[PDB]
Image 1 (cartoon, rainbow, N blue to C red):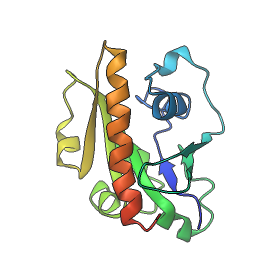
Image 2 (image 1 turned 135 degrees about the vertical axis):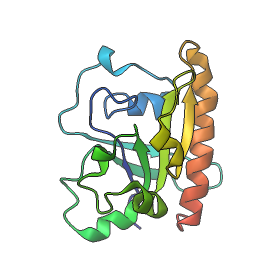
Image 3 (image 1 turned 45 degrees about the vertical axis):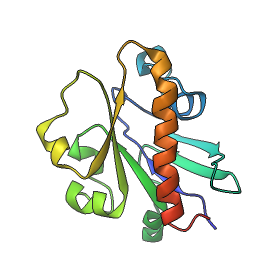
Image 4 (image 1 turned 90 degrees about the vertical axis):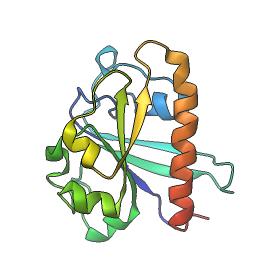
Length: 159
């Protein structure tokens, strides 16, 4: 069966972008986007081996929907990373957070000590907290993220 899709934000300011996503999800290190080039094509592929899943899963990670040529591709979106700007969702199949996050699992990544915006608290999104100063804490954060996503994959039939 087909590769699952993760949608992430395009704004180069966003905590996580196509520039630092692989380092974060695979190497277990947050890297500030300013210290990296921009990635114009807004696409990266990654592969992940899960404890409870037999075969490695190949993820398509995109910060845009210009390649969503068929509406059926929206069935393959297993996660959405959000910064809390609804405009991110403007060109999505489901453009309101209420509808979108009933359809796809949402994640809100931010730093501890930074207030989560009013509207984000109301959203059906899982909040994930990074440490401002202790980069070693990323290891636990990333393990937790993959544990969470694994349950989502299993629920969607990826075993």
